Length: 263
Image: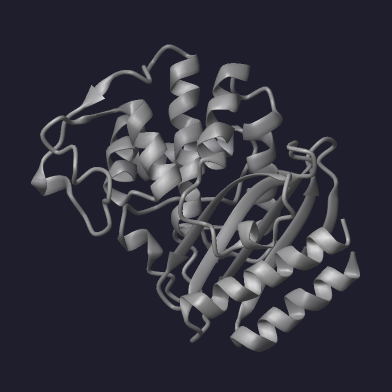
């Protein structure tokens, strides 16, 4: 609904920066509303949903096991690894690593998983192969969050991310078991409370993944809907703002409020 585009433009005025937006019908894949659908934006931690979809794809093909344990050391630890820094001695299973990457945005967990699938280059190939010809991962945590103005490295387009999340969650790319596992991880998201979740009516469903990076970059991808069932996908990205994280979050939450109001 155009009233939601009004809030997105307000967001741009408030943040003094570009805001990309997509509202997508989960069932049919129809694009209900959009703003800068085909401009590029840094993915930040939202790429972790894509990463774990690729891991799950390998599991469906029997090339990987959710229960396989992965050991690592101090040399692997990067900034913000809230879960991986605790299990250094025990190591962690692939399953535990995706949970950490998705629900806690654990950076080391993502790098560990990135290695098991062949790194940024293979994630990009996986995406292209499933029909996303624009989304690309080029670096590892934490450099992928650099968001250099105009840098296309580690970016997606709102329209592309939206349909890619749709294929991963409801398409035939993954088995029913994996699709469900991916959305369960996103539903258990623990660090996106200040964003869309803050404007969600009680009783609604939401599986999401947010991100934040340098140069005022923030973002979120999500499958949400009333009556405990997801029925639309919403993607929101912004970069270039001098605004604080709280201010960026308030803006994204307001966009969420408008989408819900005009549902």
